[PDB]
Length: 395
Ligand SMILES: Nc1nc2c(ncn2[C@@H]2O[C@H](COP(=O)(O)OP(=O)(O)O)[C@@H](O)[C@H]2O)c(=O)[nH]1
Ligand SMILES: [Mg+2]
Image (cartoon, rainbow, N blue to C red; front, side):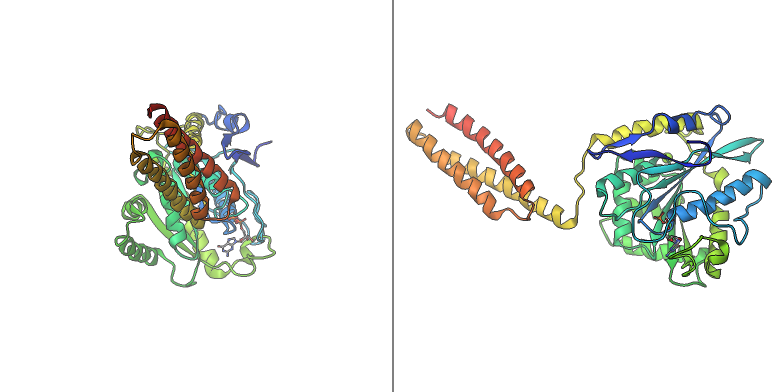
């Protein structure tokens, strides 16, 4: 693809593996015009269909106007919105991670900062594997020097559950290593009261709530640090939801005011959030990709098995059942008399074996026949091992 187009930096393959584009994306970071500039890396993550691409496109306008006149402008009132793909409706757009395929070059200290923008697949989409999207979000969190966590309406169990998962995908993703985080609450219920003091007061309330829980130590660390801020945008109005060119004139008045304020904060903060490497040196473009590769390999090394809560509950209970059945077998073997003749013992062990396979199937929970078969085969393998060793030793 040619410059000034989104390109897909990361995608997911059949087997849930994260794959980087080692050509186009790689070459994008290593262009010799800016490869040695310090970078600012802005990533956005969060729930699907909540205006992430839309917001990135408006930030992009501000970056281009900064590139041009060193002034922040969100464009003319009738200019339709373009850039990353953004669309109304329920169906899914962004898959994997997309980036704008050129940096925006901003003036800094007699030099330049190369600004890269990453747009991440939305969470809570049942057509994608949730673990896959957790990994994509964690990757965006790791590489970011400014992370936007786009939140629908308010912080809920869902957003805390997910950010805590993102921050556990290796020590690279822990809150102390996250240079800067915006908790950006879209569709804030109050179109008039959305400023910095409202947001800080809101987070202080939330910290009070989290102090009473065990579930979110990493998010709690983040909210208490100087590395995380909250911003609020009211609802944009029905001229922006549904069929829309995404124009400034289409926006609710209070939405446009908060949007202009927020985008300006982001842009003006760029020089204070230059990306750093592990050791705190300023990272250049020419080394972002190496970092992306290394952590993609880390993320591909483990399967966590994140699933729906009912399936994880069934997994816990069924794993407990397997262990109980194995222990029941072990106890049964330990209780046999050493004076029984070997062939009579083999029949008795064999019958208990079969009986315990039946017991597993009678108590296994859930309706996934495929999963049941795999677990039963594993139990049969463990029980056969135990049986084999007991019966060879028994004389
Ligand atoms: N409710 C609401 N809708 C928005 C907002 N910003 C943009 N939209 C609309 O939401 C739809 C999806 O936007 P998009 O950027 O593609 O969402 P994404 O899937 O998170 O990237 C589009 O119709 C946007 O015009 C917002 O703050 N609140
Ligand atoms: Mg860091």
